[PDB]
Amino acid sequence: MRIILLGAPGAGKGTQAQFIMEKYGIPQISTGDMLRAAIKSGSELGKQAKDIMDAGKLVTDEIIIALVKERICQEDSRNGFLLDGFPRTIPQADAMKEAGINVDYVLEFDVPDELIVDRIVGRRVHAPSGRVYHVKFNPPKVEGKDDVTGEELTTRKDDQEETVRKRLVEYHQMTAPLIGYYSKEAEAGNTKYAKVDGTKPVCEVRADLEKILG
Ligand SMILES: Nc1ncnc2c1ncn2[C@@H]1O[C@H](COP(=O)(O)OP(=O)(O)OP(=O)(O)OP(=O)(O)OP(=O)(O)OC[C@H]2O[C@@H](n3cnc4c(N)ncnc43)[C@H](O)[C@@H]2O)[C@@H](O)[C@H]1O
């Protein structure tokens, strides 16, 4: 089963990627998690990426496509995979299309800009695992601490409100057209599309996607 998650930064894609991984047993390919992993390893990728991400900009299509190609051409990607953060631009999409890769489901998380900025102030991560929490809407069971390890949570560096606002501008210019892109793909029979209300609580969003995938 091959799935793509679309939606503005903060819409809760990664939050629901976790659940979809652990309930249908397909790997999460997160471009954001891979970039943040590269910084932590201190690789060449990590060094090129850090400044771009800090500035709330998109990393070049070439680097991203190479990165995602590598991680697909690993093992256990025969049963399926879940893309989260990719594609992010039309060229990223067309590259996948031209390489002959089709997806079964394209899932869109609609959430307006207002909420997005209010959300991200409450976002907390367990940096080793990439587990994501919201202090109000999806809180850790112990304030400030990862549920699994008890390790202190941090805020992401690119989560200051200036940087967030840039990510949304980029999203509306570069990424939003992908909605049209995959609607049309769905219309031609090449995939299934579905929208959801991501403003809903995290259990109600979980529910709609059970209701959608089966
Ligand atoms: N493909 C690419 N091409 C070029 N560059 C790339 C790239 N991919 C990555 N990059 C680079 O690096 C950065 C992008 O970062 P990236 O890692 O791709 O995104 P996030 O930063 O992972 O943003 P999503 O945009 O992934 O947010 P989310 O939808 O997953 O929702 P989340 O569950 O976290 O939720 C938000 C907060 O949501 C709270 N919350 C979740 N659900 C609910 C709910 N249902 N109700 C209320 N609150 C909720 C969450 O718990 C948490 O508090 C890129 O911008 C660029 O810098």
Image (spheres, rainbow, N blue to C red):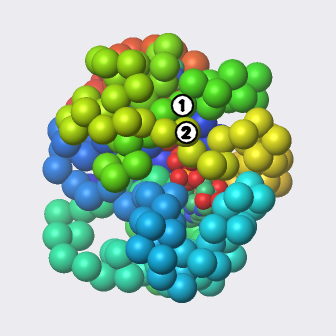
Q: CA separation, marks 2 and 1?
A: 7 Å
Picture coordinates of residue 89 (x, y %)? Answer: 67, 64
Picture coordinates of residue 86 (x, y %)? Answer: 53, 61
Give the number of the disc on residue 213: none
Quadrant including the C terminus? top left
Q: Residue at x 39, y 19 (%)?
A: 143
**Is residue 152 toward the left or the right of residue 86 in the image?**
left
Q: Nearest the camera: 26 or 155?
A: 155
Picture coordinates of residue 187 (x, y %)? Answer: 55, 51
* Circle nearer the N terminus (2, 1): 1
Q: Are marks 2 and 1 in contact (CB under 8 Å)?
A: yes
Tell me the crowding category of disc 1: few under 14, some 14 to 19, or many 20 or more residues within 10 angstroms, Cα based.
many
Find ligand 1 in the image and state its quadrant: top right
Q: Is residue 67 above or below residue 10?
A: below
Tell me the crowding category of disc 2: few under 14, some 14 to 19, or many 20 or more residues within 10 angstroms, Cα based.
some
Q: Residue at x 62, y 83 (%)?
A: 62
Mark 2 lies within 8 Å of ligand 1 (Cβ measured): no
Residue at image mark 2: 155
